[PDB]
Length: 224
Length: 218
Ligand SMILES: [Cl-]
Ligand SMILES: [Cl-]
Image (cartoon, rainbow over all chains, first blue to last red; front, top):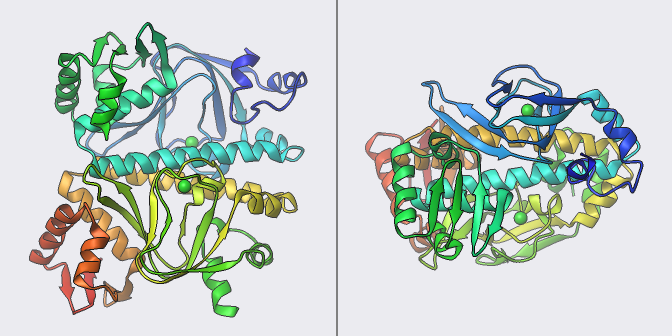
């Protein structure tokens, strides 16, 4: 749908009607759940914009441990780093649900800027937003304890994916227990320990691949 | 000014930018002075201005449960701070406070927009710069996650040495004009953790304190 796409960084509230003959300049791509869109260290000159579904963005250490940098969703762009800075992928992108996306290569993207510097503005916004988040995560890593980081990641997930459910916030993250801990960037044992405490205190309820946050207030205080 | 121009042109935002174009922007920026101990901006305040330091040092902090501030990093000559605000304006997510007298230049988003309006080729180069930087800082984040707790603080202190140190016999010499109370004020809420990492470095032969200058292995 073009409604999702017009919320995408690149073309975000620009053309009233002729936003369309450019979306058609991209053929769509459907991926099953658990599909490796691209792997660490592969060449690439393709960026993707998600129409629906989620994609986890990951790094793997020498000894097989995994970290998740971010979870991408509808309207989010990924694989953009090798577009602007040619070279191999430094991250893996893996589908966590069935995903509909749309795809574009560097030369095509370069073509859609030579008319339109406002698009470049929007892409620089996205990169700077991501730079800020990584810097905010770096600060959390050194100076916030694991439960505070669990609390922060749950609230960050809620900011992107949450929906109100009465006096509570439903956050359908589509992540496994292990993937939540990889996203936090801390041990499964200590992340599960924090989640249990927060559930016991009645701040959250863990339900499949969704969490219900009943007390965003006390959760936020803990993330401080 | 000769030497000033050189310092400015080393800023990260100018990487791969044609030198006359760098000069066309900087000639437009008003150099300013800050005294030591001056909060250039606080966490939370409206953000739309990038600074490039010509001389002096600026600490970057974030408020801790203490009411004191944790030390996130230190910026020096040729470094930027507040730079992300001109690409993605909004509240500051950290504070910037001078640790010495400082001379800097700044630019707001309007100055950026004007610079690029005439120079469409700079947008593509800026996209490369921000992307290369994001790859690097994500690489750093992941490395640090994969490191143990005390190893994280040591790596960060070593990154500061690399940025502020002069190469001297395979080691890094960092000189400062900071009192004992000014060092404690600098580290802020991070004092205990920084002190443990220094004590470890000292015990292990990594650091030689030569008064107001330190030699550190790299
Ligand atoms: Cl990429
Ligand atoms: Cl900022």
